[PDB]
Length: 113
Image 1 (cartoon, rainbow, N blue to C red):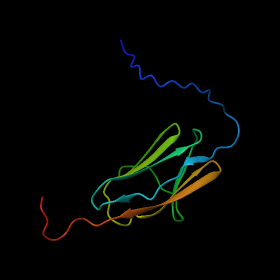
Image 2: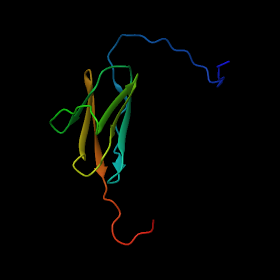
Image 3: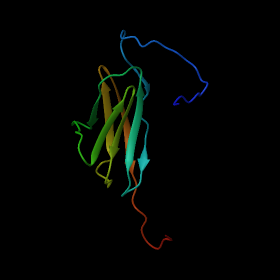
Image 4: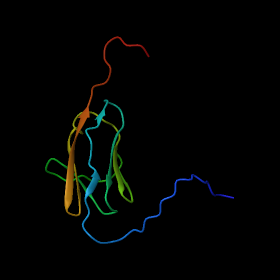
């Protein structure tokens, strides 16, 4: 019916003890103007997080799409420009992380396409 056998087997019980740390901190992601940028990070255990920018908190709406799946968080941003660039933080319970997002400029002058 519906059972895709992958082969890779590995069972691990999920406990709810001890503190939570970061396994894959954010990484310097570079995007192009007029494009779509999206960051991703993996945690040690499922938990709430907060995206900060320099010295302010961000929100989820249209231009900014916030999504989370277990221990895999991500933040999509449509309608790039240049201001979006900066220092994206991510505090999870106690620990915290920060990255550097860069926004390039669209292709100008004589170009093929």
